Amino acid sequence: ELTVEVRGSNGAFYKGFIKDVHEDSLTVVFENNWQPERQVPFNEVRLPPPPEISEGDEVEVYSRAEPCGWWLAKVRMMKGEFYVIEYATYNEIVTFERLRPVNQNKTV
Image 1 (cartoon, helix red, strand yellow):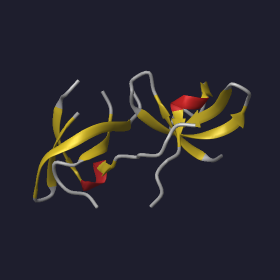
Image 2 (cartoon, rainbow, N blue to C red):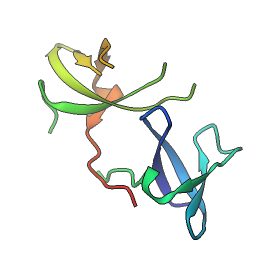
Image 3 (spheres, rainbow, N blue to C red):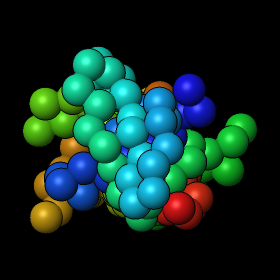
């Protein structure tokens, strides 16, 4: 039940766990898509990050258009609680919690 992250045809990255290993493919259950595991290829996977953050930096942010997942972004401002970010290329105000340093882990 080793937890992972999977890139979706959406380009984004969605928490999950490895249920099973095969030759060409992994078999993963999802967050609130547990139920259909796809069976997945090597390179679409990577590990979650283990355990600074400030503006103009590049980050991943946690959203949807559909499940929720991680989308790449840039802090183009922050102020008080709130951060202005930029994702091709919409915009939004989020908060610390919606937010994280890019996971620069690597696919398998």
